[PDB]
Image (cartoon, coloured by chain):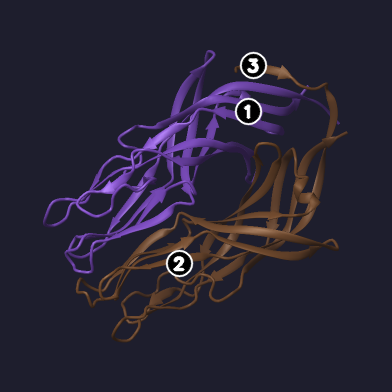
Chain colours: A brown, B purple
Amino acid sequence: ANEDIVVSKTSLWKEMQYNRDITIRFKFASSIVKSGGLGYKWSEISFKPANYQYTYTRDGEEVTAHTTCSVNGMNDFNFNGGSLPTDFVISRYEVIKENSYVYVDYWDDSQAFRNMVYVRSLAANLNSVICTGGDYSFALPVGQWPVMTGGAVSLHSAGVTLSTQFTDFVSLNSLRFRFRLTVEEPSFSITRTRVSRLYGLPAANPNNGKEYYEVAGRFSLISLVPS
Amino acid sequence: TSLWKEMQYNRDITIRFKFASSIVKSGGLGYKWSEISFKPANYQYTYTRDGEEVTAHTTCSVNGMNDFNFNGGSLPTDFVISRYEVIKENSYVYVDYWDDSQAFRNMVYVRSLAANLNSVICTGGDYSFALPVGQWPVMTGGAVSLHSAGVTLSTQFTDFVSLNSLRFRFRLTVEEPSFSITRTRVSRLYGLPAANPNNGKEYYEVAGRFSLISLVPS
């Protein structure tokens, strides 16, 4: 239909500010696929969305939170040790750099979260976090194993998106925190190759054995409330 | 204190979108492909509704895709596809939508959203795999129909203002024709592969009606 219709009687409203602490814990995931043949070649090392769930205290209440971490704007690198069946090769491996973004979707079970409605403005003041790459060994059938090591980026808050999903009957909120990246030390390399001194975070072992990365701070919301 | 009231905006909607794919060959002799995957795709267009010319933007992405593979053998000369994506009934297609219409500008303080949309069938086109020697295997077919499964309102807050967008989620049903890869044992599988999901179409279209209830100044 193509119409405009008045659904209620004029009412009174005012803007109210809400400030709340937030703790964002998340982690990456990777997909590593080998090529067939003898076993010296890898076809793909890429980032994959990863979920994390946890609980933390805020204002004397235990808050249960869920996050999903994904990346965008990743860069494709490769390593060609040669065309022989016995030459080490990585056809494609992803690296996040300053032209990439990390997104962390966040939801929590607090009444404050469910009550985010008619939000006019939302700003976040979050600490940065450094994500560093752990080692990843490439187990060749014969010979010493090349090892990817290093790499690091720091994450900096760059906007927040509030999403409200409308299904057959009710509404569910989600916040997406976007992070811009700055490359940091150490650079990454692959032992036993001439690949070294590159900056950014590869997808081989982005969590470096950590159970999660954490970004904490506060965010303020200004919403329209009845007057 | 300000004065506000709820308004309902009923409008027809035309959603045009398309897929994109990434096809990466393995280095070497030329018989191995490493990946065939879906990638997000943007589309922009204009349409008319009750006298107003509406300019719209969409971004189409998929989630829950399935990783298939074809292993013709471990010899350098055997055709292989290490990983190709297929959307099936456990997958979702999402279409983000924005338009420049006056009604869309009032979608800031939203009480509810509803959409009644037609379904659309997306069918795969052919994709040839040029081998160094021998006849070329061709991936052909595949199809899914898209069914509206919810709408999400997104508001992006950056340094100063807020940008709104709608995300339409579609659940899928597999349809005829099934897909296969000629010159191989792979045949009659159901779902839409990432090889050529647009089948030479400039875009796919889903149209219907949209209902918005929001709080606006009095």
Q: CA distance from mark 1 to mark 3?
A: 15 Å
Pointer 1 and pointer 3 on the same chain: no
Marks 1 & 3, CB-CB < 8 Å contact: no
Q: Residue flagged by tag 3: what amino acid is it?
A: Glu
Question: Would you call the spot at circle 1 few (<14 residues within 10 Å), some (14-19), or many (20 or more)?
Answer: few
Please tell me in which quadrant of the rendered image residue A203 appears: bottom left
SS under mark 1: helix
Amino acid carrying label 2: it is Ala
Residue A162 disc label: none
Disc assigned to residue A3: 3
Residue B159 x, y percent position in the rendering: 64, 46
Residue B162 % position (x, y): 64, 39
Name the subunit of mark 3: A
Pointer 2: what residue? A203
Tell me the residue that label 1 is attached to. Answer: B105
Report the side of A116 relative to B113 (left or right): right
State the residue at coordinates (49%, 18%). B48
